[PDB]
Image 1 (tube, rainbow, N blue to C red):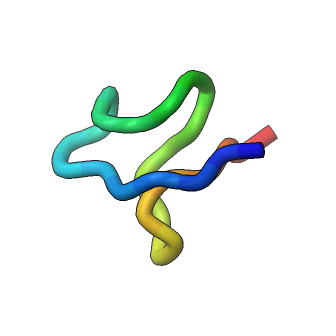
Image 2: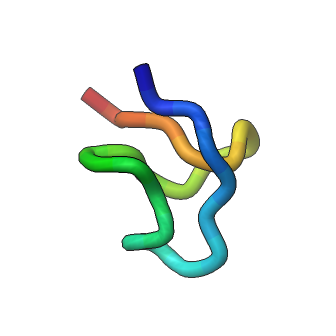
Image 3: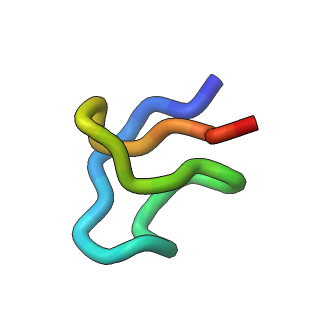
Length: 27
């Protein structure tokens, strides 16, 4: 569901967090 590339933390889609896959939801 979460697929992106963050530059900070809120640089994600929705409930995604900063991870090795750019942006991915922890939950």
